[PDB]
View 1 (cartoon, rainbow, N blue to C red):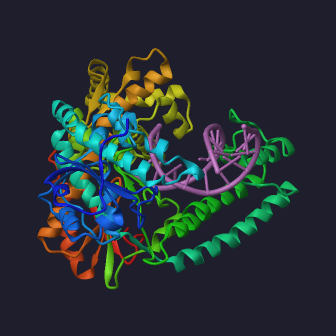
View 2: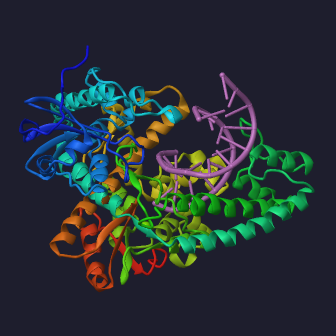
View 3: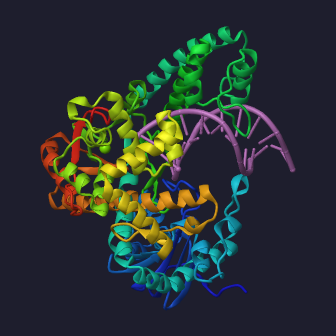
Length: 580
DNA sequence: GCCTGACTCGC
DNA sequence: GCGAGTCAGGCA
Ligand SMILES: [Mg+2]
């Protein structure tokens, strides 16, 4: 059953065809500065396996890799591109990425290897990576005969499956979406990840010194009040101290045991002095372990940078994801937490960090897709949307909007932007489910078009089996017809939410592509570093700030044209923090 | 070592 | 709600 291929000990010209399936295998989960364990090429002249030491030292082969006119089909081309970049080799000519094509067709499948993509088209002549490399501590690179057999099979799979995947994409009107958005974005993200973001480790260290000392003062206080020592970080042990020794009221339960969540503890504070200290300890400990120690661990001692990996094929919404480290959840709301952004600094001297973000892009998209007259008018006037929503659902004038009136209208808007349940809204507002439902009806009276959109979208999801975004991204909702309430409700909310959330993802992605083209046209040394959902972060020389202030907002605003304007704020400073 | 749940951050 | 990550406690 062993597939036929040539185990080459040198590169020959028939391997350098102008159309091929290419596999550049990087087995380590984190591909930055990682090894390339083997290469496989499949083309019209046959199947070949090449060793990396041979192939990546061959001037002919490396030229072929870098020749854009030489077309290549791959799975997860960003992985290969970046790993080759740490070796000083460019990858060009990728006209088809099977990971990304599988992702656009159905993100639900969770395709993470060639074998999983292949199964979609009834192709099983390839093994899953987990079956070949193993998993966990047992994860090893197998012997050359096995390795080579596996890579050729993945290449043959890519070679066979290109055509059927492009055909379905074509039928779904997702062919441009792959060739003009997702694949070009791959390249951009590859540069961003390679560039990395410079970190002030000393700053982080002296921060970790401050927390350390504070945690110790707070850890002791907790024991004194507890009258003993326990692991505060153990929900089970804390629950015994709180709810048995101190006899505190049990407000919420967990399948595991007593609930020790901040929202619960917030209400227990009045009963005992130990409660506020525990809250304080957890946030300090959250900050210390997730963002100080976690960050320091992934900083490269050589470059003194952090090189994230963006997962472009994970979410069902279409948003990018970030790992090792996740830079999309760096603390902002609390001042103690915000100061973590001071540690991110420009990669060169006399450079500054530049941040641009969309202002309420999700609500603006909603106005566009729903065509609500009132919501559209509100953004055309560039009103404070939250204050305006408070004016309508409480039937009062701007002078009359109290801070609490605005906080609650904000929560309702938030529930729409993220698709939370009425049960969700009530928990957030610390109010009854019935009142929460009352708020929503009240919002729909003020915003008839959105109500209309919610009704119509759910219906469409039921009729077609999926919902789409502005740029033709697609999400299937099988549980829409489910006869179980909670399951059906989630599916309805995802039907409502994805077109809003997904379309915003679409717009930022097209802006990244447009911005990259303009940066190049303008001959600016400025470069994309990060993407955090609503915002793009850049670094550039201070001499470019004035040009970028004008330039970067313009590109983001003109990415797509909607029925309402798009608004972008920008800032810049000596640190990411300072770009506020 | 391997899972899992419980908890918390930004969006 | 999502997604990422840390920690504990129960497991083979
Ligand atoms: Mg914003």
